[PDB]
Image (cartoon, coloured by chain):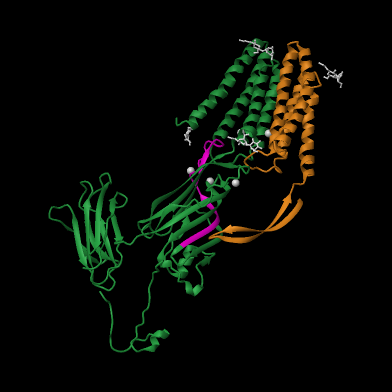
């Protein structure tokens, strides 16, 4: 291909030093710049929401002697906005003149210095935003009229969800980060190295920008807690201006999108947000690279499992009207449920049934002997399981079922006492009516409780 | 403990066709098993049989007092050992045996209640047939469970 960049030209007439690399200017002048001009014109439909109501676009680079025209127009019946042109420093070079009919605010300028580096402004500063949807066609021209954000393709993949802190509403994950992006200003000329590839290893895009003193697409994991353990870190740059970043990492992230209210029947969102650290006007995320399986299927492992992974490009505001790209890889998860209903629920059931079948007995002495004894087994079992249950400072559904379960088992002891007295007073057919009396209201209440909670916690009621 | 160590040279792909050497030293390991079957399995057994020999009794009153009491000892023991057992968020085979073990011990309490009422209704030779009735299906079920798991978890079935 053709190649690009800047050069130093030494021209010599009867001067053998010039072919030796040796340019010191001397003598009488013989040469210079050799010859409407070339024109460049651009469309863009700009949009002005409540969010974004001033907008500026840096122009790219006019020669002394170049003329610049720009025109705005309303898409619907939206108001005629304020137009102006300005240098990079903000000193004004023109203003918009609203036209003969009053439909287009046009502006004009031709160029003074050997660099004119112009900036176009359009504002909807004039009125209160009524529904925040007035949008404009903007025409622009000199005689790629606007200098555009270079386009980065980002990719992410997770290998291990290695920690979840349920109390502090955060988690930890191991994964792989790739950004690939074509910027000519990066360009390596080959004869220096003697290679196609230049490598920077073990440092942060930020640090390499600082070393090179140029702009690069730096980023941060948005909710990062403390430090990240990054290995196989690297950034590759070819001659072309094609560049790539590769980083396996192990990061700890705050996710207060946790809700543990329906534990263990809760489901959760692990979101891995990757924001840039430079605005939309310099770099933006343009593609998603499916460089590997996004979520890595080791299934035996099992503690939290994965429903679906959706990873997506979105632009978010930051300070100084920093609007910048954000690459959200967000895993959907649920707990391993066999662990809960087998280890917790099944046994619990049995403890509750023991209290219900001792109502059959009619030897209230013994009914109460077992009733009381089984309450201890309940409490006993309730702290067997207290380990896999986490302390948060608020009630999960399980904690809710468990209180009710205990309360019903304690009242069987209370009822059993009641009936034993009745037995020894010789109203034993009262106490036998009671026996069969409970036998049916009582497991009816467990079942109704459950229905209550399912509706209370699961059904948008 | 270590079963064998095999260490080996192999080349794997990386960034921009980086194909590079990898030196894998890979140890094979197993747990110290005496610790498990002595500390966990042997005692558990004993708790299991206590429930089976109280089926012999035919004083269902007392059968049930021991039956119930021994369930607590089971739960008690099950959390003695809860320390050396690690919380993962999913069932290991031990966790599997332990649930089944507890469930069978809870139904002895349930059966013991059943038989006691039968006794006081004066169908005591029903309840005595039951006694000998379990005595044999019940430790048959532990043994079949075990066979089930060995096949479920160990034998590529
Ligand atoms: C919802 C699906 O629920 C899921 O499916 C089965 C149901 O037993 C289990 O998964 C399965 O895993 C391995 C696969 O070799 C087997 O050894 C195990 O016996 C089997 O049951 C999971 O533990 C459970 O979480
Ligand atoms: C209105 C009162 C109706 C009572 O109806 C009667 O209740 C008692 C216990 O409550 C039941 O209980 C019955 O079953 C169990 C057997 O496991 C035994 O204790 C005995 O056969 C009897 O008590 C009867 O099967 C039922 O016919
Ligand atoms: C003192 C105020 O106490 C406050 O009121 C009620 C208790 O009645 C609770 O609010 C409520 O939470 C959920 C809403 O998802 C309901 O399903 C629940 O039945 C109810 O108790 C609050 O979490 C508590 O903090
Ligand atoms: C129905 C068939 C009954 O079958 C019968 O079960 C009982 C156990 O309960 C056994 O019983 C035997 O062992 C114990 C001794 O410690 C006692 O209960 C009993 O005196 C003895 O005969 C018999 O060996 C068996 O023949
Ligand atoms: Ca929250
Ligand atoms: Cl409790
Ligand atoms: Cl248990
Ligand atoms: Na984990
Ligand atoms: Na907290």
Q: Chain coloured orange: which letter?
A: B
For this rendering, which residue is in front, A10 or A201? A10
The quadrant where residue A230 appears: bottom right
- Residue A245: x %, y % from top left: 49, 60
Indicate the position of residue A34 as horizontal and vertical percent values.
26, 76
Q: What residue do we see at 71% from left, 16% from top?
A: A363
For the point 75% across and 24% down, which residue is it? B65
Q: Can residue A227 be seen at all in this image of the molecule?
A: no
Q: Is residue A441 left or right of residue A93?
A: right
From this view, report whether residue A52 is shown above or below residue A110. above
Q: Colour of chain A?
A: green
Q: Horizontal and vertical percent for residue A458?
A: 49, 32
Would you say residue A262 sits in the magenta stretch? yes
Picture quarter with ligand 7: top right
Chain part drawn in magenta: A243-270
Does any portion of residue A72 appear in the rendered image? Answer: yes
User: For this view, does A180 lie left or right of residue A142?
Assistant: right
Q: Quadrant of the N terminus of chain A?
A: bottom left
Q: Is residue B47 magenta?
A: no
Front-most of B17 and A279? Answer: B17
- Seen from the viewer's position, the closer of residues B87 and A374 is B87
- Residue A170 sits above or below residue A386 on the image: below
Residue A103: image x %, image y %?
17, 52
């Amino acid at each position: 291909t053709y190649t690009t960049g800047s050069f130093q030209l030494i021209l010599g007439l009867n001067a053998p030093q010039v072919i030796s690399g040796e340019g010191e200017p001397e003598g009488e002048v013989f040469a210079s710049l050799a010859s409407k001009p070339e024109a460049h014109v651009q469309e863009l439909e700009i949009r002005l929401d409540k969010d974004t109501r001033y907008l500026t676009q840096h122009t790219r680079n006019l020669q002394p002697g170049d003329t610049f025209h720009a025109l705005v127009e309303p898409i619907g019946e939206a108001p005629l906005p304020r137009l102006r042109l300005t240098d990079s420093g903000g000193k004004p070079l023109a203003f918009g003149l609203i036209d003969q009919p009053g439909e287009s605010v046009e502006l004009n300028y031709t160029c003074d210095q050997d660099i004119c580096e112009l900036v176009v402004h359009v504002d909807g500063t004039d009125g209160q935003k009524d529904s925040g949807e007035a949008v404009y066609r903007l025409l622009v021209g000199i005689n790629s009229v606007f200098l555009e954000s270079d386009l980065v393709t980002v990719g992410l993949a997770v290998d291990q969800i290695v920690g979840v802190d349920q109390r502090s509403e955060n988690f930890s994950v191991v994964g792989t980060l790739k950004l690939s992006w074509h910027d000519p200003k990066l360009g390596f000329s080959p004869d220096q190295c003697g290679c196609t590839v230049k490598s920077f290893e073990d440092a942060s895009i930020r640090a390499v920008a600082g070393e090179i003193n140029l702009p690069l697409p730096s980023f941060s994991f948005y909710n990062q807690q403390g430090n990240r353990w990054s290995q196989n870190q690297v950034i590759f740059v070819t001659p072309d201006g094609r560049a790539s970043y590769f980083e396996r990492f192990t990061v700890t992230l705050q996710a207060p999108d946790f809700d543990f209210l329906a534990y263990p029947f809760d489901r959760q969102k692990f979101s891995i947000k990757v924001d840039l650290a430079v605005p939309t006007n310099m770099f933006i995320f343009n593609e998603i690279e499916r460089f590997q399986q996004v979520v890595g299927d080791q299934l035996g492992e099992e503690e939290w499992v994965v429903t679906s992974y959706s990873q997506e490009i979105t632009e978010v505001p930051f300070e100084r009207g920093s609007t910048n790209s954000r690459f959200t890889t967000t895993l959907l998860v649920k707990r391993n449920l066999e662990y809960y209903i087998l280890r917790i629920f099944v046994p619990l059931f049995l403890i509750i049934s023991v209290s219900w079948v001792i109502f059959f007995l009619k030897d209230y002495g013994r009914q109460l002997e077992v009733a009381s004894g089984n309450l201890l087994v309940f409490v006993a079992f309730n702290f067997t399981i207290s380990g896999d249950l986490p302390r948060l400072g608020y009630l999960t559904v399980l904690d809710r079922f468990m209180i009710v379960s205990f309360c019903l088992t304690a009242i069987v002891v209370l009822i059993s006492v009641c009936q034993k007295r009745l037995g020894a007073v010789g109203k034993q057919a009262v106490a036998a009516q009671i026996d069969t009396w409970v036998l049916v209201i009582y497991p009816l209440v467990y079942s109704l409780y459950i229905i209550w909670v399912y509706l209370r916690f699961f059904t948008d009621h």
